Image (cartoon, rainbow, N blue to C red):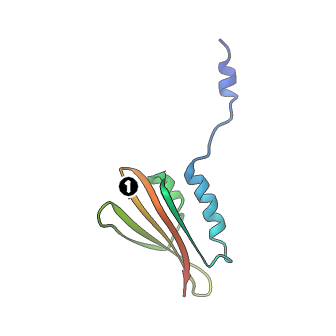
Amino acid sequence: KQDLEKIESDIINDWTEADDLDDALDFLFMEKVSEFKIKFKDPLKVTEEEYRELLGNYDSSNSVSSNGITIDQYTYDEDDDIMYKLEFTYRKEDNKIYIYEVQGWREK
């Protein structure tokens, strides 16, 4: 019954859908990408804090939400007068965020 040595020796875990998206964002945020759009047949489930981790340090935001949906917009002030706009379309119920759509683009 000393297989609990196996349990503490165990490496976990750790990946989650958010991590997987976050990793994509990493790519999609590069200076060379001018704009991307990702639509989800089945929405990408995510926790409130997982969602806050995906946003990381925007300068400003605005969101609007009629019916079950929230179009949430985020701004990242960049160099040479360029704003970066990230936008998440999502239903939330509750404490768990169901992203139906992510969009990115830049503006002067």
- Dot 1, crowdedness within 10 Å: few (<14), some or many (≥20)? some
Residue tagged by mark 1?
92
Q: Is residue 49 left or right of residue 67?
A: right
Mark 1 residue element: strand
Image coordinates of residue 39 in percent, x first then y, are 51, 64
**Residue 104 location, quadrant:** bottom right
Residue lying furthest left: 67
Image coordinates of residue 9 in percent, x first then y, are 70, 28
Q: Residue at x 60, y 64 (%)?
A: 25
78 is higher (above) or lower (below) than 103: below
Q: Is residue 103 left or right of residue 90?
A: right
Q: Residue at x 68, y 17 (%)?
A: 3
Image coordinates of residue 53 in percent, x first then y, are 53, 57
86 is higher (above) or lower (below) than 19: below
Q: Residue at x 63, y 69 (%)?
A: 28
Residue lying furthest top: 1
Image coordinates of residue 62 in percent, x first then y, are 40, 73
Split into 4 quadrants, where in the image is the N terminus? top right
Split into 4 quadrants, where in the image is the C terminus? bottom right
Q: Is residue 43 left or right of residue 33?
A: left
**Residue 22 location, quadrant:** bottom right
100 is higher (above) or lower (below) than 75: above
Q: Residue at x 59, y 80 (%)?
A: 78
Question: Count the marks: how many?
Answer: 1
Between residues 70 and 57, which one lies in front from this camera angle? 70
Name which residue type carries label 1. Lys
